[PDB]
Image (cartoon, rainbow, N blue to C red):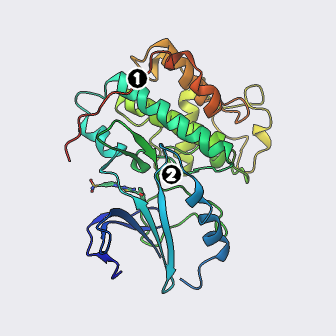
Amino acid sequence: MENFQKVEKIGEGTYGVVYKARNKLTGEVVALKKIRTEGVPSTAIREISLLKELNHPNIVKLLDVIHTENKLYLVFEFLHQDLKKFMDASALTGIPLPLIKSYLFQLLQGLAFCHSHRVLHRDLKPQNLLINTEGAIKLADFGLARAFGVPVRTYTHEVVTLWYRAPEILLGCKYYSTAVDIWSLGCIFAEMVTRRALFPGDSEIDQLFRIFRTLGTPDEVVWPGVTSMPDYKPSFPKWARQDFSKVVPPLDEDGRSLLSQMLHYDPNKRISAKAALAHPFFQDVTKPVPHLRL
Ligand SMILES: Nc1nc(Nc2cccc(S(N)(=O)=O)c2)sc1C(=O)c1ccccc1
């Protein structure tokens, strides 16, 4: 606290509040997350000290982890804007496709890296995707679900966004796979394209039903084992899959094809980050510069 010259609240993360702070000594400007205890799971602190080694250009760098006074502080490299704010600022014009494509490609590179090291994000959303003036986009605020036991409620009772949650999580699957991050990224990709959230649920059931209404209620044909999942109910309504050209107009067929593969119901059929990077949609990918007003 005395090591970081005052501050400036830049939001309230999923676990606590996030601040923009300056290293009272080095003068370094960083993002500081203050995690709000009764001892702090040594297991969690250990799994954290593992994210410190995760270095990659498309992953926000975790500089230090500091436990003190029952409070936990995570020091991260600071970026000036998040994708949620950038999308709202581009809502009237839309983000140009080359930039959408560049961001998607970089995020898949970041995910391919995390996933090859057996690390899952679990909570990807526009708010935790950070961008800079150089055209880079980075994954931040990695969630460590289960962590202490089973996270499902915050302290500030701040509403949890379900818009990007994979269907297997909603159906009660106990073990998440790398596929959950691909689903979330697919939802984000669609949102950059249409400038509207793909599946804006207000509850867990509304989230699930919004997905079903668009992609069709899943069955054993498209998703083997789905009817035996924990929260699956034979009473779910049966919606026909909607024509996909109506989902993300006016995205081209290469884009629509990749998105359809990122949104497959069966986590085992869902495309991997590595395979996605080889999709035809990225044959002409470039690295444009965004117009950022800081
Ligand atoms: N690294 C990092 N940078 C951030 N910047 C930022 C983000 C939004 C607005 C503004 S600003 N200046 O007010 O325009 C700045 S946030 C963050 C996180 O590491 C993080 C931590 C928890 C949850 C999500 C990201």
Residue holding disc 1: 286
Residue holding disc 2: 203
**Circle 2: element type:** loop
Q: Is residue 187 above or below residue 281?
A: below
**Circle 1: element type:** loop
Type of residue at label 1?
Thr
Q: Earlier in the sequence, mark 2 or mark 1?
A: 2
Disc 2 crowd, CA 10 A, few/some/many (<14, 14-19, 20+): some
Quadrant of picture, ligand 1: bottom left
Q: Is residue 276 above or below residue 41?
A: above
Where, by quadrant of the figure, is residue 147 drawn? bottom right
Type of residue at label 2?
Ser
Is residue 209 something that shows in the picture?
A: no
- Who's the residue at 73% across and 52% down the image? 175
Q: Nearer the viewer, residue 8 or 260?
A: 8
Q: Nearer the viewer, residue 83 or 230?
A: 83
Residue depth check, mark 2 versus mark 1: number of the one nearer the observer: 1
Q: Position of residue 253 (x, y in %)?
A: 50, 12
Alpha carbons under labels 2 and 1: distance apart:
38 Å
Q: Nearer the viewer, residue 77 or 118?
A: 77
Where, by quadrant of the figure, is residue 83 drawn? top left
Query: From this viewpoint, which residue is outermost toward the front?
Result: 26
